Image 1: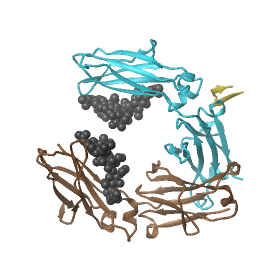
Image 2 (image 1 turned 45 degrees about the vertical axis):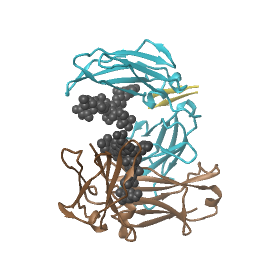
Image 3 (image 1 turned 90 degrees about the horizontal axis):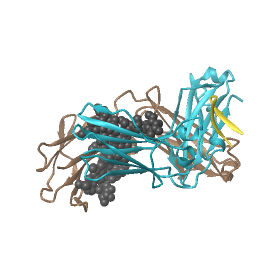
Image 4 (image 1 turned 120 degrees about the vertical axis):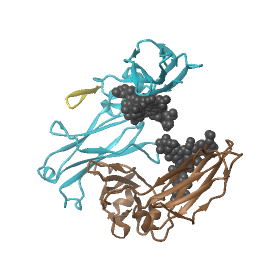
Length: 13
Length: 208
Length: 207
Ligand SMILES: *[C@@H]1O[C@H](CO[C@@H]2O[C@@H](C)[C@@H](O)[C@@H](O)[C@@H]2O)[C@@H](O[C@@H]2O[C@H](CO)[C@@H](O[C@@H]3O[C@H](CO[C@H]4O[C@H](CO)[C@@H](O)[C@H](O)[C@@H]4O[C@@H]4O[C@H](CO)[C@@H](O[C@@H]5O[C@H](CO)[C@H](O)[C@H](O)[C@H]5O)[C@H](O)[C@H]4NC(C)=O)[C@@H](O)[C@H](O[C@H]4O[C@H](CO)[C@@H](O)[C@H](O)[C@@H]4O)[C@@H]3O)[C@H](O)[C@H]2NC(C)=O)[C@H](O)[C@H]1NC(C)=O
Ligand SMILES: *[C@@H]1O[C@H](CO[C@@H]2O[C@@H](C)[C@@H](O)[C@@H](O)[C@@H]2O)[C@@H](O[C@@H]2O[C@H](CO)[C@@H](O[C@@H]3O[C@H](CO[C@H]4O[C@H](CO)[C@@H](O)[C@H](O)[C@@H]4O[C@@H]4O[C@H](CO)[C@@H](O[C@@H]5O[C@H](CO)[C@H](O)[C@H](O)[C@H]5O)[C@H](O)[C@H]4NC(C)=O)[C@@H](O)[C@H](O[C@H]4O[C@H](CO)[C@@H](O)[C@H](O)[C@@H]4O)[C@@H]3O)[C@H](O)[C@H]2NC(C)=O)[C@H](O)[C@H]1NC(C)=O
């Protein structure tokens, strides 16, 4: 899965 | 003679794959007579070569500020590799050396808990929303707040405080107009840290 | 030559009538060849004579540490009187002077709120209890915890943080076994600040 912060990409594992 | 200071990247930059982390070796008191400054950079003792010098900056007190900057890989920094800047200059009988890296220690996951205003606060024009963050290590962390996609800028976060079990905690407090809280608006505490899944978590909060 | 550092009393001392606040003039890097230090104290430019010198103490990097300590009245410190320590030593081209006093500005009363642990927090051996202290000025304060007339020692308190309206806030965190909490015990956050009624308030928290 992937995580975004205010639209911006944080990280994907 | 010249003095040397070496700064880490910013937590957010090391945690967001969409951002570019860098370490910064700043040399001050560089004299008008020997302004030449050599930089050697090492990553775990192995000399890298991709650093860049920033524009020379003359200081109001007759000295130069000379700054080399090294870009770094997210996983290297977070693997806790050691970064060394070595500075040579003619006014400096011996090269100066500095190292930083991530604080060592098993990394621990922040536990993120939100707390609504006290009934005793409900008498006031604004109320406080708290985001308690505890049990995290290292102390490198980003906390921010938001509502409906949009950032809220009216918050303050405490510096990280060392706890009795060897991990850290802090609180972030966002102050908002009572009416905004009564209006049923969801508020969200976003926390970024290397020991979280995808380096990011988000906890929410609103009237019951 | 010598360097000087002038320290304020502890917040708690100035707030309790029972304790004795003091201001403290430290002199470091006094030399072996000239260990004599002359202290002059002034309160609002008016010299006083009642300070006392602590025993001289050798530092082991070839210098002495020389402390003069001045007792102060609670109302005086709180009313924002300025304390001045003038230090003279033969190594000093001119006497060093330092001043300290309470932060200037309208004192403001802390708003004290206790916050229970989250229903998400509740699957651990211990729980966290919060005491949010906001809206106080100056930042001089003391926070302690108690339960049923006994001190609760397992807490940490953040440093005071400057807020956008120019007052401060902090949070104090008490950690207690989940059981002690579930069983309806009452825990108290106690706050001491110059702008509280009787410089003291207590708020409590229970399931
Ligand atoms: C002649 O003048 C110069 C310049 O002086 C400046 O201008 C004058 C007019 C005055 O206003 C000064 O106050 C100005 O500073 C003098 O140079 C100064 O020398 C000082 C020591 O002699 C030195 O002190 C050391 O500072 C460290 C912290 O510095 C931070 O923060 C300060 C302010 O808080 C800031 O001014 C500094 O520039 C420095 O800023 C950081 O820069 C880094 C690198 O750019 C940033 O990190 C990067 O950021 C980018 C994005 O921008 C990206 O995210 C990268 O990934 C990241 O790496 C970082 O964000 C900046 N921080 C901030 C807050 O802005 C102290 O830590 C250090 O103390 C430590 O060491 C001491 C032991 O020596 C201990 O006492 C102490 O405990 C600490 O361990 C030093 O005190 C000043 O910084 C320096 N000023 C500048 C601008 O470099 C010079 O001394 C004077 N000559 C003579 C002969 O007197
Ligand atoms: C020879 O050695 C000596 C001693 O060194 C010690 O011994 C050796 C073995 C080493 O291990 C050292 O680590 C030891 O310190 C050297 O002395 C040092 O000189 C420094 C100057 O270069 C000086 O730095 C300044 O210190 C200020 C903070 O000092 C606090 O906190 C430190 C450490 O955190 C502590 O060590 C000091 O004692 C002092 O502690 C406070 O003492 C006061 C007075 O007693 C207490 O207040 C009173 O408490 C009583 C009851 O107890 C009552 O409540 C009273 O009402 C109350 O007044 C208070 O509780 C103590 N506080 C704490 C937290 O413990 C800094 O603020 C200061 O910085 C400021 O100024 C700078 C500009 O000059 C700025 O850069 C800076 O940003 C600030 O503006 C300095 O850092 C050290 O204090 C001093 N150490 C001691 C013990 O005196 C000496 O230099 C060396 N000589 C040579 C040639 O090398």
